[PDB]
Image: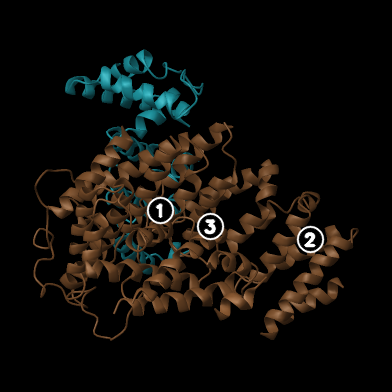
Chain colours: A brown, B cyan
Amino acid sequence: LVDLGFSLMESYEMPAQQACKLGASILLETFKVHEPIRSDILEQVLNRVLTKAASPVSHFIDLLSNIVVSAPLVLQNSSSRVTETFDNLSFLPIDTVQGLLRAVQPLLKVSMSVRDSLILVLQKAIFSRQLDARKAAVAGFLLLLRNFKILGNEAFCLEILGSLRRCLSQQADVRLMLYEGFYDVLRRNSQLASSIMETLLSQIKQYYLPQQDLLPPLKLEGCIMIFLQEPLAHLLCCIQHCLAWYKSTVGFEQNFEEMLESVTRRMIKSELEDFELDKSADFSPSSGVGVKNNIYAIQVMGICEVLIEYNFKIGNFSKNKFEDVLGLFTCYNKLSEILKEKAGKNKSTLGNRIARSFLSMGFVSTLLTALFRDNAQSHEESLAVLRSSTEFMRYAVSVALQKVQQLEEMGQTDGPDGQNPEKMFQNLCKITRVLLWRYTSISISLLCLEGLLRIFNTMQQLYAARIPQFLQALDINVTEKAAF
Amino acid sequence: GVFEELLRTSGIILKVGEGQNEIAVDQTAFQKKLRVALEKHPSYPGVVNEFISGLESHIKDRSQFKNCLLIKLLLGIKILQPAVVTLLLEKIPEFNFPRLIVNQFKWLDGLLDSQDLVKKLMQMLSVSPVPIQHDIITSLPEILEDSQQNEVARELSCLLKQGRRLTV
């Protein structure tokens, strides 16, 4: 049986998917059945697991994770391999490293030698001058930060805090992933949250440029040079998410809100003339000044999205915050429409209609519920004036349409809890109602037709076992309501 | 010495020989105490110069030279970074001492110069013998802080063209 499965897994490389599923199932069954070959099977698959560096090994990591979660102590009896498994781990991260780490995580949390060896490898990984594979190292370290418990030795954390910060001055693509991944580990500790917030405060103050009634505070020229090395929209989104979590869990936080409030106030008390991009005929593609302005344009409207999200949480039925929100969007589309991106004569609509958004799925879910079906005397007409902004209506759902398309093709998506399916599934349940109802209200409705058509195609292809929950939330009579 | 007086007042007492400095063994307490001492005693520019001279005299002493293998906290200071670099450059030709210095510089943090220490290392490799030059050059990935990546790469390619005896 084990020889058959070893042949099967390679034969899988549709029919290939069925063969891989069959091989994995028979290996899991024989591991759960054939007790005396458990150690030999584990050693053989570990030898095979690190056997296809160039070829995809996703099925390998899946089967290894299944056998490890079935028998947590199998690899413990398979010792002298926890240290060995890191031979060439930082070569081809295609999410393989993340899966391997997640599968072996119980072993690390019950194996101190493995933790020490990975710490030793961490110095070599993070200090790699090249950027071809340094992303895998930082991704693994970020996952490990949540891998170890935050009960409360704390000296371990106090030591490992500064390791990643030592590599903060890195490439923009490399600097990207820590911003997205810091929120996950921030919900696992209190002192670590303070330290991460302080480090991010230093980073943002590196670009804030405080002043009053003057030029736009964001020193956009810092990341101009040809390429860029300091993304700002992702950093600001991480800032707002970490601030929200820190406030919920319960002066840097006073500095955070003041800086956020000031920059939002600075943005509305500014215009394109205040920014470096004043005239329409200013920047052009394949131009040194053009691409610089092109990067600046890409950054600034990305910033506008983040401040929109933050003020919504702060402005609980607050017209003044809504007035700032609505005015902020007027700057966002001012760059768009006419000088969108640059111009883009290709009759194509990247990201539904706009570039990759920066809004948490919870917020856009809640924004539409406030925007549509959010009728009540509690609101102070802020929704109504928001409803007056017709382009705000179009942009309100257009971001989510890109978001669901991200989940449509890829199995994950940007924003907090994006890769959590059960958290996403609840969000998927709530969003669909307003999209369908808005169409039935009786252009804008044509957007909702795309939004629905993509939401079904996702859950039928992603949440196969979760369909009954959606059908219950749609309001085993599956056919009855579907025909309705 | 002013550096010795500041160290005794706060931080690490004056250790003799290779013995450990009389400070807490941690990057937090020892560095904070050293920074407090440096802000207190050598605060005056003349006192700052006196402390720099005392630290240089201690570094020149073989006892503190063996102790360094405090000094680490002082080098971590932003002002002490150029001083530490100058001390290392001075001790390079005069002293596996160069190998130990290269290893210490390996995985180092941000110094006071992003495009000068690389030039100093290149000059030392040009002047230094075969093994010393090879050790210095092999540290370039650590020394390549992205401050002078491309230019140093071109200069190193030219040296390789002229360096057939040390191409590996």
Mark 1 lies on residue? A179
Mark 3 falls on what kind of element? helix
What amino acid is at disc 1?
Answer: Tyr
Task: Look at 77% across and 74% down and name the residue there.
Answer: A23
Mark 2 lies on residue? A43
- Residue A451 to residue A413: above or below: below
Task: Look at 44% across and 65% down and name the residue there.
Answer: A431
In the rendered image, residues at marks 2 and 1 fall on the same chain: yes
Of labels 3 and 1, earlier in sequence is: 1
- Residue B7 to residue A386: above or below: above
Query: Residue A222 placed where, x, y %?
Result: 22, 56
- Residue B93 to residue B128: above or below: above
Report the front residue among A226 and B99.
Answer: A226
Residue A423: image tag: 3
* Residue A299 appears anywhere in the view: yes
A79 lies left or right of B87: right
Task: Look at 37% across and 16% down and name the residue there.
Answer: B10
Q: Which of marks 3 and 1 is in front?
A: 3
Of labels 2 and 1, earlier in sequence is: 2
A73 lies left or right of A193: right
